[PDB]
Length: 188
Length: 188
Image (spheres, rainbow over the protein chains, first blue to last red):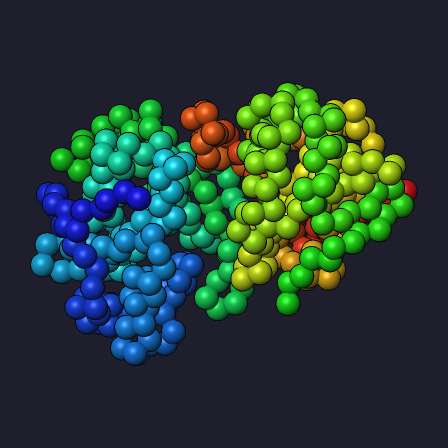
């Protein structure tokens, strides 16, 4: 099993261990539109539900959550999914509030981990899964350098009961020099 | 709940719990061209290597194996991988000895589990992961009814360090009626 840093630093945002202390943020920054294109959505528009949300995220083995901090506020959060050492691969899922879409808070969130994955963890693959209904993340990831392999029809189930069409993305190791390159010039 | 019978009677082949006693068959038709583009492949043409191979299949987390009996003799084997009743989906891995390629055995072998999944298990998804290099199996799933969703670049690492490009195929619950008619045609 690999080791993931607790806190990160950049020029726009800084990551840190996602704890229940950031609960108040998710409370005020609540919107049924932000939690409708994710594999895991809250139970109800209440503190009790949102509280159990973070508890579950920090519950599933292998996943390490982080709180995206765009300065003094909380843009959102990001974590790693299905960390597979033997296969030298992993997954990354970003989630930023509506009032934070378009800001580099999402660009660095990935950049920070992508750098720790390939350069440090010596990863060979980093896939991303976004709902086919959410063109937002799609436009972003595709404008990030990731390759849109395809879409897994009804790959997973939605918190509401329906089925989700996960669009699989990915960034090979030899593709890092490019992605990182464009980002350093896209952010810095 | 989800369950997999031990017997599957067919007009061509019959499936049964893949036991270790079915070893004399694999060692009888061991061909490098078979276990070439497969995640599961012995280390050498010996009864000792195959022994650690069979046990590996029957000892995989929630994986059921079956022996494709074609004409009072083993023609190959089929199994269900990643049985995830949660999202109502599952994978199907198949393989047959070279001296058997061209027989309805392979087609019917899947047909039995395909219907038992959609009709019985009321499944919603059934994906098939084949090697990008293994073009033979690819064209085989084309006539079956599987849809080409995409190819996972270096999804998994082979026991030799070589990365494999697993191609993703699948059949929706609404596509069964069509696929079933595609099999019963050549099979019957």
